[PDB]
Length: 102
Image (cartoon, rainbow, N blue to C red; front, side, top):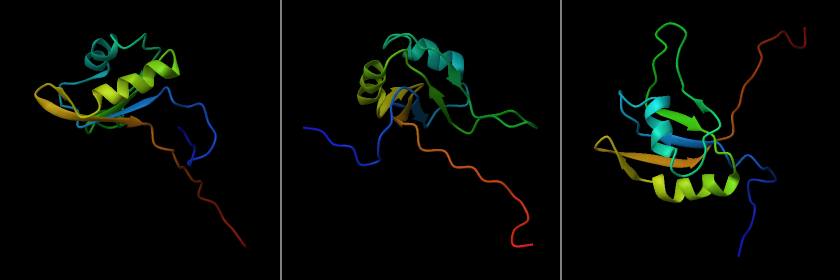
């Protein structure tokens, strides 16, 4: 049994981790997800003024299957004495400001 609502895509490698701690970083997440498979790259949400994170990040998996397995597990897992959430990366959405109809 299976089905695709969202649509058609193969971007099931980048996982979204939430509920992270103030000490958790790309490094902590790496050695924390290194078991599942072989992380290809990691991204951390930071600013240009403070360059700090709110409590989440995005991890990539060498494969898709490995990622799915990481979610089913890491999902509502226990990290640093906290409950983090894991799920497929949400669909981004950007825009551009410009003059219209004049």
